[PDB]
Image (cartoon, coloured by chain):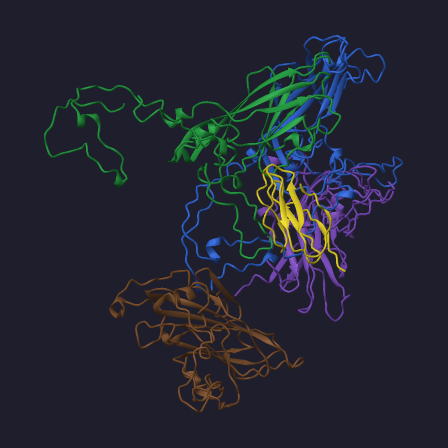
Chain colours: A brown, B purple, C blue, D green, E yellow
Amino acid sequence: GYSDRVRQITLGNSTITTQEAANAVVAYGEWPSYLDDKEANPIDAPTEPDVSSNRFYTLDSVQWKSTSRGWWWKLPDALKDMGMFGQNMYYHYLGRSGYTVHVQCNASKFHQGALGVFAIPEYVMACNTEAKTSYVSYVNANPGEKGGVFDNAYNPSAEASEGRKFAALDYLLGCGVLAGNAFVYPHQIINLRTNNSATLVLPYVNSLAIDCMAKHNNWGLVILPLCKLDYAPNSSTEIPITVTIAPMFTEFNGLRNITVPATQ
Amino acid sequence: GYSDRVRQITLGNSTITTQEAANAVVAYGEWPSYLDDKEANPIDAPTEPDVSSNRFYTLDSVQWKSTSRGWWWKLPDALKDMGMFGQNMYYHYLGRSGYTVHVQCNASKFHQGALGVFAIPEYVMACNTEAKTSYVSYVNANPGEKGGVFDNAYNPSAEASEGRKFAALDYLLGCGVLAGNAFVYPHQIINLRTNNSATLVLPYVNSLAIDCMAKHNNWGLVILPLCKLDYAPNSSTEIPITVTIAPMFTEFNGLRNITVPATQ
Amino acid sequence: TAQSTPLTSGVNSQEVPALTAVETGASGQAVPSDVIETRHVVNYKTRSESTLESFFGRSACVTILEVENFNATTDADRKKQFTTWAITYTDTVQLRRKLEFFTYSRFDLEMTFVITERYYASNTGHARNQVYQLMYIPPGAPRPTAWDDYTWQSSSNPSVFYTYGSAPPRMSIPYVGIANAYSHFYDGFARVPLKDETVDSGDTYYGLVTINDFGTLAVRVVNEYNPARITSKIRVYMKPKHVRCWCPRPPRAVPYRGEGVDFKQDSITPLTAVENINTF
Amino acid sequence: TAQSTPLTSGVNSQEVPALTAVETGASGQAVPSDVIETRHVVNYKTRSESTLESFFGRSACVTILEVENFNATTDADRKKQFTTWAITYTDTVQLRRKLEFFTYSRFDLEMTFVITERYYASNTGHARNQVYQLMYIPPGAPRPTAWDDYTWQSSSNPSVFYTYGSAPPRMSIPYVGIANAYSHFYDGFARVPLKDETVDSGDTYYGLVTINDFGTLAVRVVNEYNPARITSKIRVYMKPKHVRCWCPRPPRAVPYRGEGVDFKQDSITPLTAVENINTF
Amino acid sequence: QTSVSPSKVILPRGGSVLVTCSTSCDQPKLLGIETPLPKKELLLPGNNRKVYELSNVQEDSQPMCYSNCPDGQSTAKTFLTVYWT
């Protein structure tokens, strides 16, 4: 009676239904959970925002053209201004969170294309200057909601001003590894003849037990167009990719006044 | 193995098969049956035309354009000239009958439209004159096979001659109730992306145990276009609605010579 | 009671109750525990007032009858001395609309008669206290021609004699239908116009009004003529009790224009047009 | 009963009940057996009348309604033919003050209607006996525009028809609050004025009066116009029974000036100044 | 249901317009004038009658004056013009 293509996911007061889905990837075979008492790093009383922040948040819909080359989001910081998870984050020094990334892109049965949806632990990217090394600013490394785009050309700016940003090169995947090897990460491929949604379940992955979300970006969401979009009547059409992310099993420590980072 | 979309209905020597059907509505949860002895109104010997009139009868196919506004049939009198049920009817004073209304309309996967198929007990309509009230002739109220059509305009004729007919207004459903409330009747909706046939099973509904079919019209079959037909290459196409009705569990009383009603 | 609400939490599975198909004829079936997360709410609220015995449990008004009492000289003055009313529930628009929810109904009817008086002129003397006859005439008994004929003596017709100033008279009329339920809507005639009639019944009325004869309520003033003209008003009431109903229907939207289901041209527009579709 | 008094005698010990500390919030707790020597007094006196079922067990007066009955010609004369009263307990100052002891209350309400009449002029004839309609209009049912429109026929609104000269009509209205108790005092608005509204709701009324809709009591005279103008007065009563109350408050000291808790400037001085502090 | 007495107003650019909007009820639950124009209040005794003091009239405006009587939402506007040389 049941099928693998119809899936409803509910967290808090938010619901995603999908009728042409592929199967869901639990990353590295572990469902996210709270910090156990045998591994706890801080000793303060942890805040568990039970349903106020364990819910789906819908980002901005980027448009996937025929010349679109890729997108990237840093995952505990693309939700920095989303409801109460953006208010649980900056009022606390520590924070761990599991995730349910759901990437939404659909077309007709006459379109074609592929979207490698990745989820990269410690997605450290390269700077866009050759004056200095490991050299990216804070605003350019943490865009938040809008994310960033990749590029099919590496043009390092000789200015140290405009070179403090990610040299988001698509075939080297930012960090100088080939993109055809990126399938060792937890990944799904949106193929516009088979499916229309990619669902990943991401546990908290870090060397520490719990860490500052304001400093440290745990996961990296990556969407690569493997085969470009090609619609035969209108070759320059645009189908939107909408990313909907939920925090899961969040836990925070060290309450204080609000942290407001710089914007420039 | 079995599905809800493939259904064969056989009564007598007639068969309807359908391969894209929705589920069937038994009206008010009761399957039609013969008159039980604890409720019998007449005392004569009842004629039970076992297979000679409990069979499917195919009416005329009306054409559902983009400007078609509705159709109506009075149910024990749209079969007044159909085989032996039209000969069991006028040779008897009393008659009860269950029904199996099957409405047939199909298009491609590129068309669109909706058809509210209703079945209204005691479908009393309004006259098309303001000279008198409750004022409809016999021929204009009982067309028989061809049925009638609705209209999106109420033009009461000042003549009492041409005003002796049903003021078949679509949004007031004839009787001055709003059409969006007509779903309290036993209904199905033919939607041209989901199904292509509407099957209802109608028991004998009347205050009496058995009644004159020549006088009294029990049910009212109503087909409203909710969303109009729209085919994008040919905007003025026509797909036919064919109505196929079977009497069920009929029973007649009071045999005499033939009743031949007036035709003008 | 009504249904409570179970403590449910979020789901991620192939069991999808949020998606139905109304082509099949069934309505929606999702209760709010399906699509969201709900707490536990013990529900003590009952639906006791919405039942049909309490939905019709009011003494509605169905008509207003007028009789007078004076020294009648002309013939029109002798027809003000009494009033015969054909019994129906359609002479108002509020008990009718509550009954045209349903196709067929079965109820014992309870009536009560609230009656007022006035002086017509000012200086034409006075009058004594008055007694009012209300006689239920079944179909077939002779309707009164004058106000004091052989018909008012009521050797078998049910009559009530209300002394003015008392509590209003009340009585219960049983289910008197010749069917097994009162057909609120009747989709048919009274006869069959045959082929090649010389009768030419091309004026047979449609539908309901050719089968209902419930009676005639004839009201006189039992007094003779006082010196002062006393004009009376009588408000016949109905209250359906022991109510059963069958086969529901949508309620009346546009106004009436008669005893049928007809509707007048200048009021075929019940809605008021909103500004746009996005108006809260 | 109330508490008796034990036979105690004098003490000399460290147990000191005469000294308390009202900084802690608790009141005094010394009964007279503590600080003096007392006899044995068996106390048979009970507090049975002071309970809330008997403290509110009177049919108070809440308003006075006036209707008339005459040949109306102008438009102001047609608005004397009926009277619509918004139901509230705040139109007098004595049942209100007994209810503003308590913040929240829950009670089934019992009303009784005591009705008088008079002739207006002297030599304009006479009139017959009169029947009075009193119709309870819930919020949403159409309030009457004229005295004889479609609204008075009351197919579902609860109406009573009082014949003048009888015992006064009485009825019991249940707990009809949409909360779990009637908020006598409500410290809040009906809506939230948002940031940068073009609505500019800078005239939203404070507090209580923006949440209470209990209905409308519309009263007509069921008669037509008599030759003599009959002016009537109707005194709507309330008697809270099955009374529960919560969260007590101090009683009203200074007079009222509206439906709120407001107070007028010229009566902010309820006390009378004594001669000095040493005046017995 | 809702009455605006200065319905036809002529007044030049920049000046003040006195707008008197009340209702035909005894309990105005929610009553106000919808315009993006500066106004404090004007003093007027009575729980029903009401005057807002508009100011800095630049263009042609049509403010809506709602009133939440217990029979639905009501609507009344006023018409005002400007002057230029």
Q: Residue at x 35, y 75 (%)?
A: A205
Q: Residue at x 68, y 46 (%)?
A: E76
The quarter of the displayed image where residue A122 is located? bottom left
**Residue B154, position in %: x, y?**
79, 48
**Residue D169, position in %: x, y?**
55, 21
The quarter of the displayed image where residue C277 is located? bottom right
Q: Check the image and report above or below for B11 versus C53.
A: below
The residue lying toward the viewer, choosing from A257 and C275, is A257
Report whether C125 appears left or right of C113: right
Quarter in which the N terminus of chain D is drawn: top left
**Residue D10, position in %: x, y?**
12, 25
Q: How many marks?
A: 0
Quarter in which the C terminus of chain D is drawn: top left
Q: Check the image and report above or below for C208 versus A137.
A: above
Residue A6 seen by the camera: yes
The quarter of the displayed image where residue B95 is located? top right
The residue lying toward the viewer, choosing from D195 and B9, is D195
**Residue D207, position in %: x, y?**
49, 42
Residue sticking out furthest to the left = D12
Residue C173 seen by the camera: no
Q: Check the image and report above or below for D241 versus E67.
A: above
Residue sticking out furthest to the front = D276
Report whether C65 appears left or right of D56: right
The residue lying toward the viewer, choosing from A169 and C22, is A169
